[PDB]
């Protein structure tokens, strides 16, 4: 016969970074022309 | 007498593409206790 009681506290922290990029294949850029 | 003649066709695929990336850092601490009786 054996009986035990287990107590514990768990602590943790986190930290994250992200980076994204989106593109449209239909309108990918806009052009400007200098004319005379 | 006026007519129209077509020379070539160009297709612009209306599509949207995205790219994501990330990083994560973590750290856990646990201090367990046990009292065994027999």
Image: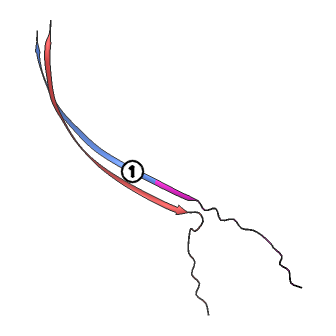
| Range shown magenta | B1-19
Q: How is the image coloured?
A: by chain
Chain identifier, red in the render: A
Q: Secondary structure at mark 1?
A: strand
Between A36 and B1, the residue placed more toward the observer is B1
Q: As displayed, is residue B8 above or below residue B15? A: below
Residue in the picture at 86% in, 80% down: B3
Q: Residue furthest front?
A: B1
Residue at (15% x, 29% y) in the render: A8
Relative to A21, say whether B35 is above or below.
above
Count of picture labels:
1
List the single residue furthest toward the bottom.
Answer: A36
Residue B14 belongs to magenta span: yes
Quadrant that contains the C terminus of chain B: top left
Q: Quadrant of residue A26?
A: bottom right
**Figure quadrant of the N terminus of chain B:** bottom right
Name the image quarter holding residue A3: top left
Q: Answer with left or right where residue B21 lies relative to residue B6.
A: left
The picture places residue A30, in percent across and down from the top left corner, at 56, 75
> Residue B29, how many percent across, how many down?
19, 36
Q: Main secondary structure of the magenta part?
A: loop
* Residue at the disc numbered 1: B22
Q: Does residue B4 appear left or right of residue A16 in this picture?
A: right
At which x and y percent is residue A33?
A: 59, 84
In reply to whether residue A33 is colored magenta, the answer given is no
Dot 1 crowding, Cα within 10 Å, few <14, some 14–19, many 20+: few
Give the left or right position of residue A21, taking residue B8 as reference.
left
Letter of the chain shown blue in the rendering: B
* Marked residue chain, label 1: B
Residue at coordinates 69% horizontally, 65% vertically from top-left?
Answer: B11
Query: In the displayed structure, would residue B15 be above or below residue A4?
Result: below
Give whichever of B19, A5 is nearer the camera.
Answer: A5
């Amino acid at each position: 016969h054996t009986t035990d009681n287990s107590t514990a506290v768990q602590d943790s922290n986190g930290e994250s970074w992200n980076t994204g990029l989106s593109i449209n294949k239909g309108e990918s850029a806009y052009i400007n022309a200098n004319v005379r | 007498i006026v007519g129209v003649g077509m020379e070539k066709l160009i297709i612009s695929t209306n599509e949207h593409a995205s790219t994501d990336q990330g990083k994560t850092v973590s750290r856990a601490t646990t201090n367990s206790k046990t009292e065994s009786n027999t």
